[PDB]
Image (cartoon, rainbow, N blue to C red):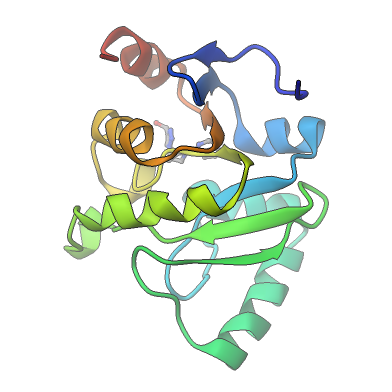
Length: 167
Ligand SMILES: OCc1cn([C@@H]2CCCN(c3ncnc4[nH]ccc34)C2)nn1
């Protein structure tokens, strides 16, 4: 039993809710919240900008030190950093950004990072300002992640479309 509430069950291990991931993280304080990161961990907009803003920019400060030490992530890769006031840990995962021409096949590699964590609160990777089709992202999630994932979808209209079209 866990504290996630109001989710629709899609499969054995994947759950979905119309929710603001920032507000959901604040309330659940999950072990792991996933950030929709870029390789530079520049958390300017989308989910990343919202998560970082909720940490009062502490996520960005920590991220800048990480990059200065380690260099950029790979597209499809991830790193574990602090969850600050939102979660124990933040798993920063880089999905491909279609608006940069990155290969959508890397979306599966991106979701594979979730399998290193037993339970996660997450957005749909490569959705929103990353330019991929969220219906496809949900399909890859379901077909790749084997651990327990609680997906937060900000837009109510999109949430309803994702549920209604789910196979
Ligand atoms: O159409 C509106 C819309 C845009 N996006 C992008 C794409 C990926 C998912 N998403 C978020 N997912 C959960 N929480 C959030 N808070 C703030 C953003 C957010 C950001 N999603 N819906």
